[PDB]
Length: 498
Ligand SMILES: O=C(O)CN(CCN(CC(=O)O)Cc1ccccc1O)Cc1ccccc1
Ligand SMILES: [O-][O-]
Ligand SMILES: [Cl-]
Ligand SMILES: [Cl-]
Ligand SMILES: [Fe+3]
Image 1 (tube, rainbow, N blue to C red):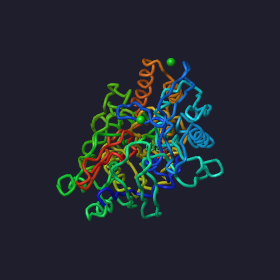
Image 2: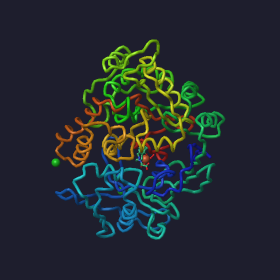
Image 3: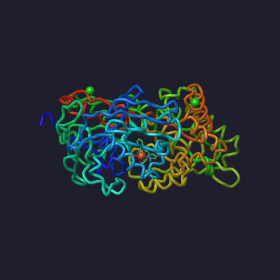
Image 4: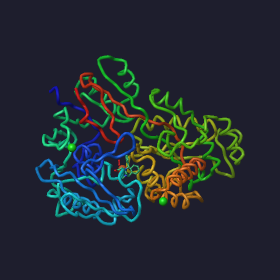
């Protein structure tokens, strides 16, 4: 019991196929599967399964020297055959990985020997190693657990080289993990971790208070923020709030009336009292966001001009673009048509509902009629893929995704960001520059390109940045300080030390 912990997650961890997406949970995939190279807090990668690498002048050709002491948790060796088999299994599903540009860059992968793995690329793709460090999909299952020599159609046992092993999984109840006693690296202090399936935020908070669970770790939706604050004050409990990890924002549809109008999007960026929204819906626990990426994100310190909360300026912009108040209605019209904007969100999510109503109230004050469209997850996702939205809640991806991979993704037609940007005349140019920036090794041209991309996106008011949000922890005191993992979607259980 003293080196075993119980914690919670909103759904099961999934089958833990290392190469597929939802319902697999990334943090669980990272507990079982490892990358060639490991991301660090400081933005670099260090050696991991690969102990060294070289790259051609090219540098389109890469040669990794792997550790020779690693075994999958079932005793089978990790070597360059296994690695290459994994990359093949991922790339037989190439289409599915379209959002990750490394998947389109990989041209060939080949085991030169047990300890040498060669990977060759379409281009001198700068973010190569960071993308290899990601939870998915470039991590390694024992080949012997492939189904008919593929992973794309399912796996057998989810055997990784990772510091944790999936002991047991009860659909809709729990998942139990156990420390890998034959890990190649440092042994975790925790021996057993039990994940209780609890989808309701307030039910999570209760399970903590009653003592049923020892740990909660998540983003701003981990538990009600008012309860979180009450906890921070009670010495019976332990709580933490990290520094911001990523951005929460609306995406505005530049291709759909009335948000197709620059002037309208500029006003919207002046209408919301952000600090009050945070103080009112997020119990004062998050930070205001003025730009797509916080100035602390790499390449993102551009001196971009915030739009402060300024109702009067929002009105003026509206009036000048011809969106005026009829007698005696509170909602602007121009040319027949009322200033009506649909804001869609997952309607079961109380926090999203909560922020939307505030957004709705603030924009009413400047003569914008926002109708709330709260729908189930899938509908929201289909609107995202389709561009069937005026405004949609959205969020950046945290490190190491931010900003390169988030920017990379704007190019993919089925993503909310591509759809929002469709109305821009500059859209092809941006997508071209996103492509160039990812292959640039002139370091000054790289800065210049990100500058152009982010600036164009800022000045077009594609987004309405709301908050830079944080990770948060609630824990039994006996567990000690809980660390944060470099990768925002990972959970560093192996650094927990009672
Ligand atoms: O899924 C990933 O590995 C990472 N995701 C890659 C893209 N996703 C692919 C998919 O989910 O199929 C699709 C996706 C698109 C837009 C928003 C979120 C999404 O998951 C990005 C991500 C990073 C951190 C946290 C959440 C999502
Ligand atoms: O992908 O979450
Ligand atoms: Cl070593
Ligand atoms: Cl170059
Ligand atoms: Fe994803």
